[PDB]
Image (cartoon, rainbow, N blue to C red):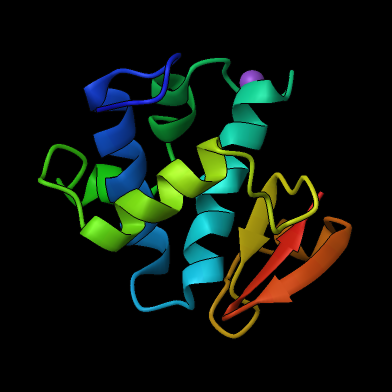
Length: 123
Ligand code: NA
């Protein structure tokens, strides 16, 4: 069922992480969050497994919210497989935030790449 390099649990948790962050966003915004997870895996500055990236303490509200082991939203799951298949609409982003609600002081310091739906994607 799952791309080589990933477990069933990897894909489910990615889908649940993506739904947590981007439920209701344009489909492109959901692929984008998935893209960011894969970019963080690649990056030296984040963990180097999908689990490690998803379980970073503040990172994905699906973790704190008890959603990471649920049956995944089918569209968030498609977005995940789209990103694994090489769709990265964020231009290799590592960070994102919603400028209307974000309360982080430091997020505004990241170099901004583009905005998709309610999220600005950043290096
Ligand atoms: Na990494």
